[PDB]
Image: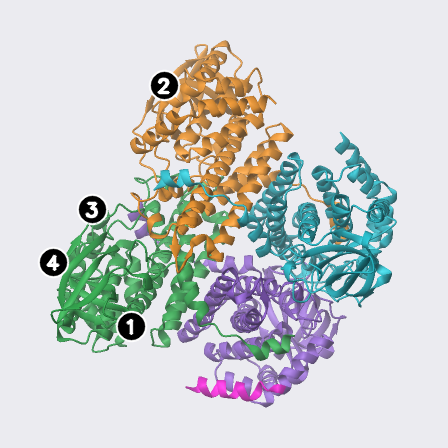
Chain colours: A cyan, B orange, C purple, D green
Amino acid sequence: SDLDDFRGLLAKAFDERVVAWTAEAEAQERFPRQLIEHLGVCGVFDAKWATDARPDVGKLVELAFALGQLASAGIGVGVSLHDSAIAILRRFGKSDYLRDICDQAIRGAAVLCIGASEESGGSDLQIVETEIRSRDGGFEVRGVKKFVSLSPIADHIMVVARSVDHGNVAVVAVPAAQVSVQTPYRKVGAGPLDTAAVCIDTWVPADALVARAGTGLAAISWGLAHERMSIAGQIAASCQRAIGITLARMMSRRQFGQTLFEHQALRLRMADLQARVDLLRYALHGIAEQGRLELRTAAAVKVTAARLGEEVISECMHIFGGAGYLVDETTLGKWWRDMKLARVGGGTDEVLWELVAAGMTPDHDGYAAVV
Amino acid sequence: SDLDDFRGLLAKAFDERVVAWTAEAEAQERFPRQLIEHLGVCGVFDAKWATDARPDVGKLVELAFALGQLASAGIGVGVSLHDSAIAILRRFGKSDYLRDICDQAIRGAAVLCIGASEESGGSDLQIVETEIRSRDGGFEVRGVKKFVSLSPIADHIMVVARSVDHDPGNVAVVAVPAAQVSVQTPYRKVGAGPLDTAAVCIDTWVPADALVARAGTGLAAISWGLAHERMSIAGQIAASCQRAIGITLARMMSRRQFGQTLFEHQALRLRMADLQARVDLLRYALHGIAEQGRLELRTAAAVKVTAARLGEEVISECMHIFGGAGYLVDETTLGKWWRDMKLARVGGGTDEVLWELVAAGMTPDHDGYAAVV
Amino acid sequence: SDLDDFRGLLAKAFDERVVAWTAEAEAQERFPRQLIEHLGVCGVFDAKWATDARPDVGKLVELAFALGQLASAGIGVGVSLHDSAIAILRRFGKSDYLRDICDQAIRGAAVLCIGASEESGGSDLQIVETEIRSRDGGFEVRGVKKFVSLSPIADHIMVVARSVDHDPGNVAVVAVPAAQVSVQTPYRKVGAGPLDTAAVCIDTWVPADALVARAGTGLAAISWGLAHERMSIAGQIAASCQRAIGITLARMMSRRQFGQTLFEHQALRLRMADLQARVDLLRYALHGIAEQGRLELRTAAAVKVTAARLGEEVISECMHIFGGAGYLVDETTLGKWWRDMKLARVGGGTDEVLWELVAAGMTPDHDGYAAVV
Amino acid sequence: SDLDDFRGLLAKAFDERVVAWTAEAEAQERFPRQLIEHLGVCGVFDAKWATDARPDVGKLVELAFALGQLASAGIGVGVSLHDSAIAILRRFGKSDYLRDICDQAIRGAAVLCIGASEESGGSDLQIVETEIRSRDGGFEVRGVKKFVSLSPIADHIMVVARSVDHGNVAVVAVPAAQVSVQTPYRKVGAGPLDTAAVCIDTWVPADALVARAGTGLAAISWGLAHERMSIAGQIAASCQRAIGITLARMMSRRQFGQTLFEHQALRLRMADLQARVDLLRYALHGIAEQGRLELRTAAAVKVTAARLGEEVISECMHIFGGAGYLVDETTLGKWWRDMKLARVGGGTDEVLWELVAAGMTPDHDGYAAVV
């Protein structure tokens, strides 16, 4: 019912101008700041967060489906990253300074982004080279972040740093004016996901400390769990959209006297992918039903969805034949190129499988009964 | 929730004696009739069905997990088949005779089984050779059914038949007592030992009140029972896979090779983490489906084919991690699990038949297609 | 062996300047005509073809590996297409006009391309809309061809056409000069940048001697060229996959994460060992096929679909091991490799069409079946 | 031509009585000793080995196809194991005692078998508990071997042992009369592959030493490479046989108005498996063309074939539907149960992938050109 109202709100906010902003963002290969401002103004982040310090997984999942329906990794990932930075601030931001930047972010007045990954420490955030040092009642933050999505338009960056004065990982919020944003990378896909290296050599007040030394990894893991749940939801919705488009093609394209849908090998392949996509969507509902954000569950669902998504898009692109390979005839290549980011961005398959494995429990009694 | 009370009831009924009966049933390759009687006497079918004509998918799923935890396809499948035949009677059985047979089945006083498959028409139930003909205010029933699981112990068989009085639709479902059928010698099978399956020869007459579903409603009646069955198979797979993963992890954490435990070998660890993530996804999906609170033919078809294919991979990879020991019948039971799981892609609807059901309800997206071209 | 001398010749022709032309072709997204001229001038096509009407599969395969080593679908595919059109002329071109065009193509004086695919009939070449009609001792040729690779630089197009003088078989192959066709603007494609592909509009007349294959022999002529092409695609995939595995292993042995190099992470190591074993198997299979010394339509179909599907997996998994860097176009070329490889399952015959060819020649085993039942 | 004569010889030796011996062996779940004696008497091992100390891979592969055609893992594996023990003796057996037992084995007068695997050290043969000690000009050999195929009928066992007097691994030939063969195991499949534990507590002459301490692993690896090439050949032939039987079923079984072969999803699935089985067979010809037994190539081809074989048999069994699951209606279950041994017996996937990985070479120059 609060969820039915949230869905009603998403249906009002995700209108024809959002679809138009998405299409233009794809053509320009840049994130439209007006989307976050529009979602903020519409009360999307406000209705999602309400007065809770911890996220409502049901609302998180419904927003992920809305983003996924746009079939644009850049747009969807961009919004979800902003929202995941909000999740870090809501749970870990104690100062009035942080609660105010968090409120600005919920309103869509400030764009937030994550500064975790580096050239050396991409998957391993423990080997972070970015340093945080206490000086003049504030902090000195120095380092380079490799992949900072939304950095060309962000107002604040959630920087993962290693404290010189002290595990040892901390999170510090740094304003955009105090960082050097490099030229955005030319990437394989996800055009509107403006990603660039960020060079930091500045000072920040003590109030800008999001998570103190020895708590930074818990804070970034919380945001990454929030992000992983969203990526899984976005994959489920974008895969459903791709299956539906592919089916429309299959029912109109005729070859060897029959439509493609009448060719049983293609029909049953699609039915298998549909069944598996439906399973992922039902699983997300099932996870939301528990009403808690769990790090291992988020890791598990995101890796499974990223690997399924890759397959769905590859097989949809295959069914479009030659036309699928022609950029001015179909957009399948763009979908396929965007989806390839899923297994790497937001945590690699291996890192996520290590997190799942770490919490797996043996059954000694059952093993005793089998031997 | 009434669901927490149902779980509490399942925890009471699925006791150490049930575990022992399962083990004995495996050794004897015979279904233990006492399990259905026990579940009936315990109020399991009664609490699941209550006064509803249509099933509570949450309770259906919880019972499937309890059955799945036993890691025995014969035991789990046999119970689910009895309960799916109850689902057919609850929704389609109109006569006082059928409602009484149905009540007996809920009590565990009568064992029901399904006689759908034939030598010719296995997957295609429209091409059933078994005939039903109106005679003397009743019905003549003649035919042979090939894969009737529980037939050696059943009291009534839900027979799918083609009406000769009607024009081909034609399909009907008729309840036939055990005494009025000839059950053949049970088949030696690849696995699922306690799932007593045999051919059933029928040449009999039954009263009009034995008609479960009249000509042209028979396929809907059997599809309803099969949807109920498919949801249960998926839950049994999710639970049995979880049990196998847990046992395999215990083996991995004790077995040492090349100076490390198997769990310390990253290639085995990540492989198990991927299987775990996928079995978890299936379990969450079953909860997601149950929350919708309705039994849908296509959803049941889609979850059972997915689970069957996943379950085959999980058991094969768990068996592989047991190495040579996995191949020794008196050292480990992994081979039995693996042989049992191979039935999942065929029994209760083949992958292809279930993918055809899924495909039949798939809808094109014209607006999105207009945007891509 | 004449094969060792052919390898020696390939080693001389595939020099640092060829490598540089490849790089420039990638940047410009234009096929370098000079490569075909260079290969012709070097005696590559001449040594491959000698005086044979039918191809030497060993030399075909060796040339495919040389092309594959460049890790560029456009460059490799463009050369192979020119050479496959030579295969059609060598076996089917009877007139002095065709033998001269064929000799020019072996010298690298004339670039040949294939005009088979249409907007309607892409995979099904029996439903070609392009028509051929006898007129004034020659032939009228009218139609549109959709995917003509090399058409912006070709001198002659091998056009698959349907004869209106004959009864539907009907299919013919006719050689049409570049000046007598209208080549459309090349398509922007997902990958294979230097593979200049465009639609070709035809409404012209040609002499009788331009007839490559008369009505009812056209499908055999195009299938012959496609079989030659498919064998080459498989060899190009085997070589390009080996190059990708070698580069990825260098990255794995230098890149450190969680205190170890990537190669020291067992899950990545075994994954690469499995891909290596499978690419090795494909390379050995190509040698095995070449030893048979004959070009077979079904064997070419079976090896190309297998290789295309294997190659997609190899490049996707190599790209994955490059992590974020794999996704950055100015840091690594893995994305280009991956985008190029996606063409393999569609260009030169889709998986489904090739599996239909394989299936058509599959033979049942009656004696074994009698022993199993 | 020597190969054409070898094929001609195989066609004469693999007759109706060999097919009858196979069928009876399956029913009895025991290896028919008369098969090895018959193959010996026919000159099969003699023609294969000639006067060479190193195997002719072409002849090795042709014999593997003959064995594979029988569709019986027990029979085929049994013969190949005998022949692999011959390979160890031919290259490593220096004493007249060993050359004579080797000649007896080629004649089919003596059945040989391998005693490598143990309860603790299955995949890791370096951690072997079986000990070899020099005493009274001979050797004292003490230990237990877990999986010794053909042990109930063998005359000599090639025992992998760790020398107390001394890497440290050795191979020693022990006569059957000097070992305690346990009751054969009840196994998942491969019924006629009589496998049992072997308890050794005996003394042997110095002449019985096949490979001295520090050479035993090279000797067992040579035999295992010979065995792996044969397993790959057997899988290729048995998979071809299964595809052909499955196709006969598909062309006679009618469902939903069409034969199974007319159902495109099943047809294209079979075409894919056929294409892949043909690729494996061509690869074996390609490997034989190099005319050398290579440890890594044998490891690579066997693991690839074992994994393909599992898939082929599982999918053939699926196409037989309910009938496939009925033991008195079809033999698909037996094939499926036999094939499951391929990924474990003769080296596990992981051990074989470690051997392949160990010889993989990086391309530094190409990597320099990509970055």
- Can you tell which mark lies on residue D177? 4
Do dots 1 and 3 share one subunit? yes
How far is disc 1 from disc 2 in space, using C-alphas? 71 Å
Disc nearer the start of the sequence (1/3):
3
Question: Which x, y percent locates residue D54?
Answer: 27, 76
Label 2 SS: helix
Q: Quadrant of residue D122?
A: bottom left
Question: Which x, y percent locates residue D138?
Answer: 13, 69
Do dots 2 and 3 share one subunit? no
Which marked residue is nearer to the observer: mark 4 or mark 1? 1
Q: Which residue is mark 2?
A: B178
Could you tell me which residue is drawn at 47 percent across and 46 percent down? B314
Which marked residue is nearer to the observer: mark 4 or mark 2? 4
Q: Which residues are magenta?
A: C1-16
Subunit bearing disc 2: B
How far is disc 1 from disc 3 in space, using C-alphas? 41 Å
